[PDB]
Image (tube, coloured by chain):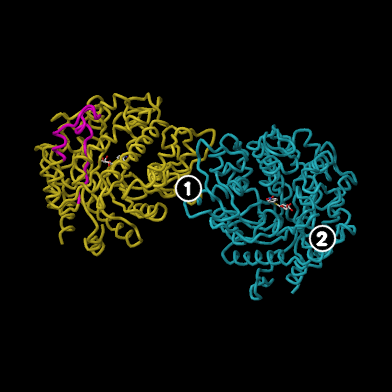
Chain colours: A cyan, B yellow
């Protein structure tokens, strides 16, 4: 428990610093088939394979923010947030996913109203163009980001970005092309736990007929090409002195398992395959050496024209930080054979150190362990190794477990002191990091709202605002939310 | 030019610290076919391909130390040296290279007399068992260290090692199984510049029917297996509290070419492929990750019983230091394709930095540039990453160029102030390194005598003592030698 002289204060951090909360379309919008919205990959996945989501639920309603957005802004204003990060639904804007299919007027209106309302209350909008919701039409036509032609998906995504620039560019000054490329590719086509549900034969997912060692890279390579085409388009027709564009990386901190230098090497291969995978190409135009040396031919190459577009394609970078892991070395030998794309790093990511203890206290769900130190390590790598570009912690928080056999009574849910302590500790390390020369610019608490947690369904509540599903999704502030309120209000 | 107060004094190092000079059998011995000595790979190479040595010479006489050894010890005593490092001629001991062939009595006698004489003058002998001189009989029988079975050469070397332990074990308290494995394998089977003269088709060497991307590793792997087997035998039937055994690595310091982090990575792959190649295996029982990930299947795997034998097989380690290089990154791509085994490091070793200036001033020959800092960097890596074992700089010095076109007059030859300066500087860094916690134990000036410089023939003089080839190889102390004399006597 933090002492008083230790609780973050707003006068720490300059006036520029922005504080806000974040959400993602499919996770909170609901109205999956209303006002012309086209079906998405997740609509498709949840409806055809509820056994694949922990509690057999879907997000046909989610937090119902499509109809309750006005309330969301109200809560944001009341908390005194500076910004709000949300994503746009590709299929709600382009039902068929293509330029051919046409632009859905109702989709444009919804985001238009939200953006205007946000700005009216002094809340700066940070827009995530793509947050895993792929138009099923594009998925059936060519597998989406699996597009073997590496063209279709790029042209389509680009247009989708264009439409967004065309209708929201005048009000939006902060764009994020993609969210968590690594999580998306590794989970959708590696362990098949996400959206499509594909994985290598022998593995356990809905469609075990893919190749966990190849598809994640194929998809990731297309995303990168798409990113480039998009930023090139943004900089040539929409960029303004006061507007910025980038993308957000998912990343866990990596600490050497033991004292051996072999683990130090394992740690580096880990940062490389998790963060470097997508970060290095947007900064220098190619993948990390370790990956090219290990994944070999399974990692596509970029033409020279592509290398140019990629390198330096951002004005800011988003970082989604939740935990860390101990990286333990795995030697190269004729025995060991990678199974998942992530095993190409020749290192196991342990939760418990050699002393049998967890890297940090368990926050409740099956993977979040508190280790704010890891967020400092990350900010120092961005500063000393990667040009120290503007950083935004676009995601950070924990998920309070709430199941059938172990229901979370509302009163407990609102007294999320564990979440409060977590948020505060990380905010503090940013103040530390800034003084250490980090170029961090803002912090977004992940989940303004309790919502659909992908394959976890509604078994976890990540919001700072509670959402009562038993009474038409009416929201209530938790202590974390209340603390954030006085923090921005003091 | 080095000022006084900066010039190293003997009282700077502990009384424990040892100082000496070094040589190698083929390079000085001579009497290539006397008293039953068997033909070696170099006898064979020089006699059949005089065009492959700069001045078309051989070492049939060399410094004729086989007949003048008594004089060599005298010089050593006069200089007040603590030790003398020399190597034994495998074919002079085992004419046919095998146990079957028998032991040559005269060969035993020569080394026996030398060792006794050395000890009589208080000079401790550091014996290098193998210094590139492979019996031609084995070379012809199965290609020597190219032995595809990874059995014959290991078995024959071990016996050779045994014979040495049997006849000199009682007097010798310091053994070195191999000398510069890297230089030997890379030059003999990589560039084909050494002994056998083998290289890949497409390259230029005596026998371009080999494979520069494989044979060096094959030979290196056998050497390692051989080393392990020799030390195991030593430790079980010969080791004594006061006796030690190890090997000597050739190694150039590596400095990042530029500021990009990519060069830092290139630097590490360089230390790895140069030093790590043989060092890591004797310290932890296996080649470094980088190499296994880059040379792939071209680098043989060690059994488990072999990993155990290899790990820890040494009580001390020898280091041969001459210069350093800037390591410049090379990306993996469909264009670049390694040709030489050393290319597997994906890094060019530049002599001049980004500013067009050499890493250090030139010492005369085609490759020695003065960079004492590199030695410090090397001793720090040994101290911090590899267990900080007792280290001996078994080689260090420069080569005064003396050709037919630009001959070096004896007067200039003796006034080797450039060498003296160079020797003094490195001895100082040793003192700096000790103060930084290095476990260095002694220093050996490379070349007590001017001698045959392999493919360079007699175009370079490395000795601290001059050898007049026009007057029966009579020796004269150069200024460097004289300085070393007063250094040890104060
Ligand atoms: O180990 N894991 O199973 C896992 C690791 C990272 C993430 S990223 C993060 O996961 C949140 C919780 O599932 C979700 O709300 C956001 O959309 C995402 O950015 C998801 C799941
Ligand atoms: O790049 N090169 O040309 C080169 C580098 C290192 C060495 S090692 C050293 O080379 C000396 C002169 O070639 C010789 O006297 C000794 O036997 C060896 O230890 C030989 C040649």
**Image quadrant for the N terminus of chain A?**
bottom right
Q: Which residue is drawn at 81% across and 54% down?
A: A404
Q: Nearer the viewer, residue B433 or B108?
A: B108
User: Which span of residues is magenta-colored?
Assistant: B83-111
Residue underneath mark 2: A118
Residue underneath mark 1: B263
Q: Is residue B321 visible?
A: no
Report the residue that reaches farthest toward the front. Answer: B237
The x, y position of residue B137, in whole percent, is 25, 26
> Is B444 on the left-hand or right-hand side of B122?
right
Q: In this view, does B166 lie above or below B415?
A: above
Q: Which of A485 and A161 is in front in this view?
A: A485
For disc 2, the chain is: A
Report the residue that reaches farthest toward the left. Answer: B471
Classify mark 2: helix, strand or loop: helix
Q: Is residue B414 visible?
A: yes
């Amino acid at each position: 428990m933090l002492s008083p002289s230790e609780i973050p204060q707003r006068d720490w951090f300059p006036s520029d610093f922005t504080f806000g909360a974040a959400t993602s379309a499919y996770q909170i919008e609901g109205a999956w088939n209303e006002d012309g919205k086209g079906e998405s990959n997740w609509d498709h996945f949840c409806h055809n394979h509820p056994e694949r989501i922990l509690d057999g639920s879907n997000s046909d309603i989610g937090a119902n923010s499509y109809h309750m957005y006005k309330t969301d802004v109200r809560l944001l204003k009341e908390m005194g947030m500076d910004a709000y990060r949300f994503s746009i639904s590709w299929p709600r804007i382009l039902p068929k996913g293509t330029k051919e299919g046409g632009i859905n007027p109702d989709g444009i209106k919804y985001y238009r109203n939200l953006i205007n309302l946000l700005l009216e209350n002094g809340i700066e909008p940070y827009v995530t163009i793509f947050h895993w919701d792929v138009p099923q039409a594009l998925e059936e036509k060519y597998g989406g980001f699996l597009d073997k032609s590496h063209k279709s998906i790029v042209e389509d995504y680009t247009y989708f970005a264009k439409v967004c620039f065309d209708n929201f560019g005048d009000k939006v000054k902060n764009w994020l092309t993609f969210n968590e490329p690594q999580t998306f590719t590794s989970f959708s086509y590696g362990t098949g736990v996400f959206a499509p549900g594909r994985c290598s034969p022998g593995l356990d997912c809905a469609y075990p007929t893919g190749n966990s060692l190849v598809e994640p890279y194929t998809a990731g390579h297309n995303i990168l090409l798409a990113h480039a085409e998009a930023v090139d388009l943004y900089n040539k027709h929409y960029k303004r002195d006061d507007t910025r564009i980038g993308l957000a990386f998912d990343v866990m901190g990596r600490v050497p398992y033991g004292t051996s230098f072999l683990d130090k090497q394992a740690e580096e291969r880990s940062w490389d395959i998790n963060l470097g995978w997508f970060l290095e190409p947007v900064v220098r135009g190619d993948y990390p050496f370790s990956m090219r040396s290990l994944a070999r031919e399974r990692l596509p190459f970029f033409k020279d024209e592509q290398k140019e577009k990629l390198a330096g394609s951002y004005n800011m970078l988003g970082l989604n930080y939740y935990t860390s892991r101990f990286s333990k070395n795995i030697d190269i030998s004729p025995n060991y054979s990678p199974v998942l794309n992530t095993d190409d790093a020749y290192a196991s990511q342990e939760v418990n150190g050699p002393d049998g203890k967890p890297i940090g206290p368990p926050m409740g769900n099956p993977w979040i362990y508190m280790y704010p130190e890891g967020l400092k390590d990350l900010l120092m790598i961005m500063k000393n190794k990667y040009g120290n570009p503007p950083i935004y912690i676009t995601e950070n928080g924990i998920g309070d477990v709430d199941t059938k056999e172990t229901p979370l009574p509302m009163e407990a849910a609102l007294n999320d002191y564990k979440r409060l302590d977590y948020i505060q500790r990380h905010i503090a390390t940013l103040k530390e990091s800034i003084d250490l020369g980090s170029n961090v610019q803002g912090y977004f608490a992940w989940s303004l709202l309790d919502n659909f947690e992908w394959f976890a369904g509604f078994t976890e509540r990540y919001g700072i605002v509670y959402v009562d599903r038993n009474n038409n999704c009416t929201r209530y502030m938790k202590e974390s939310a209340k603390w954030l309120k006085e923090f921005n209000t003091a």
